[PDB]
Image (tube, rainbow over all chains, first blue to last red; front, top):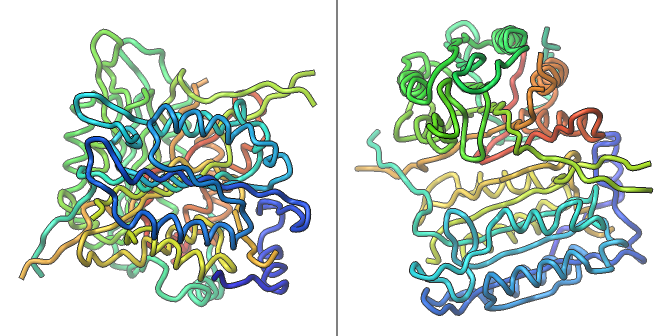
Length: 166
Length: 166
Length: 80
Length: 80
């Protein structure tokens, strides 16, 4: 479903910027990996409807962009941590040129809500933790490689409008 | 000291993207404003040497980019707040197409150190506060106009390297 | 001999915090990725998503680009 | 009749947290602004600054681009 890049456009992009583009690996040998973590059903927060449509869409897109997609559902912050640490240690990254991480859940200012989250008992994955687990120390396989993190963490705290008259 | 944009390059940029570029105002009538706040001398933190060279450089650059530059020095977080609220309310913004804000100081994770900052008694301007005071509600004159914020807030907490062998 | 490497480099985050309420953000992101992966680096695609949300219809959406340590342009080169 | 407008839009932040120690960051930023304001939008100039810092010589610098709500490309058009 993705509009393809022509070999002409590819060279045209490479001509406009010399060594300013991330190198891509051979299509036939590369092992691109992506991870989607979607929290739909919660202990104390309302059910996220449209999650299945969102998982489906993102999965199909990332595959069509060349990625193998792992899908994990309804995890606590502890489970997400374990899943992310495993993902960083995946052998496929060594023969990959990039990765995508997609988070779909509820959120707070600090981070992403796990399945067990409540105001009385927090279940939160910090944004800091995602970058830490995927950084150069913890994930040397993705060193010098682009790491795209997409976070949909729904907040009541979200901006936000101001009303005006013409 | 800035390499100039040719009228050819200007049209070439406008042809590559249709309505995807911020509009610039008439050179002869526009009143572009920039604010530099530099904290060099502190109550409890070491003196920031090279501040005068930094002020000079940034001032000359922003002027050569078409901005009138206000320079404020050695302020507390309270003083910075007052200065920023005044800057948001400046009449020149109405006839400007953009602004620059430059902060040069010590920092913590949350924000920028005022002149009186210590671990025992905090003097901190939050990053949130800068955006709030310059947002659409508090600064409607800069609505739909690019607001560039450059923050040099020196931290011991700063990243940071990992050592490896080939 | 040991060599220095940046602890954190080559990251880009795209963040939506909009209440719920597929979802408007995800759908719009898929659409722009489908259309512009061929011709635009990821950061530009994120900007274009924001542009499409410029007029606040219904619930206002303005997803931010955050914590960018990309040193190069990331082009997807779909088809390759 | 009242109209809705995004509370926060058209911001871009460029952040250096590097110890001190003119300063390396500011000097490097001035240089890239002088050289690329004519041909590159501000976000790209920020990326180019990062690229110049790719090899950690001395104290490592990797200034981040943060909280981007720019919907368009900001070109300085120096000379205009």
